[PDB]
Image (cartoon, coloured by chain):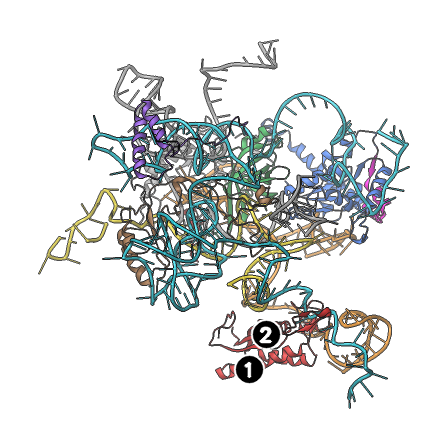
Chain colours: A purple, B red, C green, E brown, F blue, G orange, H cyan, J yellow
Amino acid sequence: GIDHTSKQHKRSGHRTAPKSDNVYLKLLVKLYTFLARRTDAPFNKVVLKALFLSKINRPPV
Amino acid sequence: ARYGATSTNPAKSASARGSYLRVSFKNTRETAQAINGWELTKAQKYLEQVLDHQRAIPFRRFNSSIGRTAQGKEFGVTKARWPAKSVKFVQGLLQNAAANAEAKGLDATKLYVSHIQVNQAPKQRRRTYRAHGRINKYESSPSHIELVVTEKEEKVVRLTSRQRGRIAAQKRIAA
Amino acid sequence: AESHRLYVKGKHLSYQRSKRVNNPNVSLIKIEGVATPQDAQFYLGKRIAYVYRASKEVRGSKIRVMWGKVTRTHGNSGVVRATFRNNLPAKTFGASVRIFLYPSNI
Amino acid sequence: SAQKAPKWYPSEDVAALKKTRKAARPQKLRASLVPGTVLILLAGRFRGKRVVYLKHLEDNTLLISGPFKVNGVPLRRVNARYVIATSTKVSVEGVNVEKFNVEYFAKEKLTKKEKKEAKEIKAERVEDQKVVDKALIAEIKKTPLLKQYLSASFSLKNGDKPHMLKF
Amino acid sequence: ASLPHPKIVKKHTKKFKRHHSDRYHRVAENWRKQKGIDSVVRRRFRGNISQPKIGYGSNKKTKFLSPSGHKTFLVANVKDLETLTMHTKTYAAEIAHNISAKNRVVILARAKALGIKVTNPKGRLAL
Amino acid sequence: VEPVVVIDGKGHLVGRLASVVAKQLLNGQKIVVVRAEELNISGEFFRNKLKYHDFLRKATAFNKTRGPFHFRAPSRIFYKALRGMVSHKTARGKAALERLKVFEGIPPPYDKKKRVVVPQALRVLRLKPGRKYTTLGKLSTSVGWKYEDVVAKLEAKRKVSSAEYYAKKRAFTKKVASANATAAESDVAKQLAALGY
RNA sequence: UUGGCGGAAAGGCCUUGGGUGCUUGCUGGCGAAUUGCAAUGUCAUUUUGCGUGGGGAUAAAUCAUUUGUAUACGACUUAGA
RNA sequence: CCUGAAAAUGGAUGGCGCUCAAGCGUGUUACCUAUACUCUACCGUCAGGGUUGAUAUGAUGCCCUGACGAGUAGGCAGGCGUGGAGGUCAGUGACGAAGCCUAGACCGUAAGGUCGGGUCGAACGGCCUCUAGUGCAGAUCUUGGUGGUAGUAGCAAAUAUU
RNA sequence: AUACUGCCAGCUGGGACUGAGGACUGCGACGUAAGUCAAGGAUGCUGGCAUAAUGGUUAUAUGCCGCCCGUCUUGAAACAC
RNA sequence: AAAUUGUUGAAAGGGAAGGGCAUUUGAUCAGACAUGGUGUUUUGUAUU
């Protein structure tokens, strides 16, 4: 019995993998999960997160 | 004919079957259970005494709210009856079994009722009439009496090393 | 001699229990002539065997044994807890257990 | 196909055992055990037999021989935990026990084929027992009544408590 | 035999029989969590049956293992059995219940020749 | 250590003896109680008479036959007191009472065998002097026991029989102690003396 | 085996004398072993079921019939070679 | 402490009981034991991470570290099972498919799955997906059947039969 | 001096439970060093058995616990349905 | 098929029976390792 300051087993609230089944998309994420883990440049980290986004979260540019 | 659970051999046995017999099933079961395991001659004489009220069939399972009698003291129970219909259906089958045994060539002196069994046959619907114009079922309980009569009739020792050493020890020490 | 007792006897008093909950894993053994827990400290680790007469021969012998060992003292009355390979049948409450002197400390 | 397939097949190889930092340091005995003491066997064939402790073998066992001419316990090894040491001791500066070791007690090279499904003391054992017992008996005669004491068996009588007994 | 594995313990062996499955014949034996407002099983009272939990989950290194240490793999024909030829140590073959007696003998003959352990060698033998 | 131990009831308390007895029964020791009518109860005699009459007041209203059997014999009032100190409703409790036998006087074969007291439950040792104690024999007498006199007229027979036993036993103890004294002051006896015996 | 005593649940106790086995009260002499380092390492005490070989004795009850001091039925109470 | 102190089934410090207490007051230690706390193992969830230059089944994978785990209404996730559809296993099957029974075995926490034995006679499965008239203990549920009650109540108006 | 309180990177003895991981890395100690090690988790030796022996299923017994489920309800074993 | 019933067999039963933790007892059940195995002269060289 512990005083739970915060909720337990709560998920981070962020996508970890693309909910989409697109096999070619998962190839890009597979590459960039490698790049983000094996480069300290925040560019790979931010682009990896932006690939997980949904259709409305990726608005056309 | 797929008889009941028999512990005998078909060679030294004779059988009689009766199906859809319009007899009180509950009264028949008690009649069958009474003679169960008796030699045929004494059982046949038993039933004759039952008609003439010299002896009473002990009612052991289906016995609720039936009156007491002195003739049940033979069987150790205070509840016994003389069901005439159930008996005459049984001795008719005993005579059939005896004839079957004679036909198969079995000794008359050693013949005993090894297995006797009663089962509830399909029950014939009728129509009683109760108060306030209500109809209720008024139905029989026929019996599938079956019985078979038969003639009468008349490991590795492991040890441990300690144990085997012990069994050798006591042999050699007390000679 | 007339006495071949290489062991010391004990009584299987009861399971380790609360007021209304028992634990069959831990048995309580009361030793003869033992009163203080300090005195019972000599019996820690000793092997306990419960010996009972079986129905049929099991291993070329009519007897059977359930082995155990004293694990800790229990209270101030010299009752010692015992852990058995297979727990006591719970019918032997107040029965006799044999408590040998090995593993000998002295 | 009755069962479709396992996609991930476990590897058949055996993983090498991690290096073990568990050496075999020599075993110490209880301070009450001195070569030449009179032990009290507690377990096995010879329960309750007083014996004489002779040599601490490398097998972490005890080479005891309560003189065979007295109690019948042969030259045999026992376990240091199933024996009770006693304050009494006997002089053993006249018995040779150097040749005693593990393979002198090597029972029999048993293989899975030489197994008897149904169910002769070595001359070397007896003669080597004699030359030892000659030294044990010769020394034991100086102290009185100990030969009788060693001959007799030990038992826990009624009403005496081993927790408060001194051996 | 099988490749080395830790001593397998089920962590629970008695089957989780449904509440009152003995009491009422209509209540099947298979487990159904009692979801009543007053259910003592749901409320986890002392002295009542244990409901299945995730704590009872077997060791992941010893899951789907028969006590012999082999994972049950259910084979029906020769070619499916040819799949395990290099995995004798980990998988054991079980011939399906609908494989004919004349067809088991070729499987059993092939399995013993390939070292595959079969856990029902006596199934549907004629003698 | 005895396979069965015979407890004398003279000078004991019903409660304190019962609890000691009840524990020893469950532990497995077999106990037979003798001279239960010589039991004592702390509290003046009339106080306990009310305490029993209040107990005798409890009868199953609709059928007094099946109610609490208010036994009056000293053996059974003590037996009642020991029940409730043991879970007699279960098999373990039933086996415990089976190992218990409570008697009036000292019936054979327990007459010719060593009686035992519980020092821990004695009236002398546990009651502050001056406190009124109630004899169980006098209590049972009032509450309905009809054999208080006959067990008395027979205990007198047994006591003189046991008294003659101790007459010849004390004569033997003189004989054996005289032999021990004569066989003392000897080289063997002196060596045992310095030995520890 | 002389006797006794013991009726509370006696079923036990005591004694005379004799034979018998052992005797560690003292001194000897011979055997122990392989149960292989422990595995209670089995020795008790109830109840019968088959048989050995002696002893001892050689019926009742119930049903059925009947009687009514009894009685719903049982039961009870009678009588009947 | 006593009187004050009287309620109706028999009766309640829980009971037995307890009198230098086993009561009241107080203090000392010793001791007992919760699913509490500590440590370890395992399950699961979450979190933070490691893991691709001929090197690993090619990553919802594997692994490491850590913290937690109650739960109705309710929410979400991963799964099991049923009727049928597309594909596949050139799947199984009259030498026996389905079904049914099995205080016989095994797997899974479980939904369930598998195997053995018996009856049985003609179709039926595993996996990837699709679809739904898809999972029952209750609804004074529907239909069918069967029980205890129970060989019981009762088969006694109309004078009566031998 | 001793009591009490406290400290020891003081020693030592006994007892219980646990052996998770599976090449190597690392921290470190002792070693002049070579190396060994109680240093990022148990090894060594011995014995018995090799099957109902351990274990499982089931039935029973015992110790303790266990109210009859669904639902309405603040509240269900309810003399609520 | 189940309810339900009979027979046989097994088991238990002092105002319930049934269930859980644990073990006894009885009944019943799978596993070892007895591995092609540190090889061992083929009776005109694949049994170690």
What percent of the width, then of the height, locates residue H125? 38, 56
Residue pictured at 64% horizontal, 46% vertical: F92
Magenta stretch, overall SS:
helix
Check if mark 2's residue and mark 1's residue have beta carbons within 8 Å. Answer: no
> Which residue is nearer to you in this view: D88 or D26?
D26
Using the image as rendered, state which of residue B143 and residue B170 is in the foreground: B143
Residue depicted at 83% across the width and 42% down the height: F54
Label 1 sits on residue: B96
Q: Quadrant of the N terminus of chain F?
A: top right
Magenta-colored span: F132-155
Q: Residues within 10 Å of mark 2 (few under 14, many from 20)?
A: many
> What is the three-letter code of the residue carrying label 2?
Ser
In the rendered image, the vertical position of residue G60 relative to residue D16, given as above or below: below
Question: In the image, is E71 to the left or to the right of D159?
Answer: left
- Please say whether residue B66 is visible from this viewpoint: no
Answer left or right for F93 relative to D37. right
Callout 2 and callout 1 share a chain = yes
